[PDB]
Image (cartoon, rainbow, N blue to C red; front, side, top):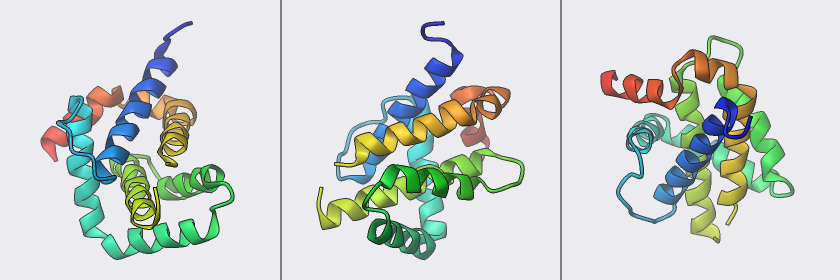
Length: 148
């Protein structure tokens, strides 16, 4: 139905990804939601824990997949998740990577964000719909943050 569960999750994911991309692209606003406060903290924390690997994958991605960043990104996301139990940590890694892309892009030029956020929303809100719901939605992410 209109604004079903999948729709609400997709929209929420989309705007969370638009926030983090903005956050990494030199924009400074208070977090628009609790989930955004959580992601900004956890995604940047994960970046510092692996800065060279994310920066290296990001540069390679930009230098290889300029033709269509979206379809490469879909593959990257699948490989970030891998074959094991999915978890909020894996989800965070998706945001981290895309935020590093966004910042490296701005150091070089400028706006693929619109493309990137939708691609994230389609993958998590669409493909991984079942895991997201099973794990409480973005509310469950906020709980994961308030105990991490």
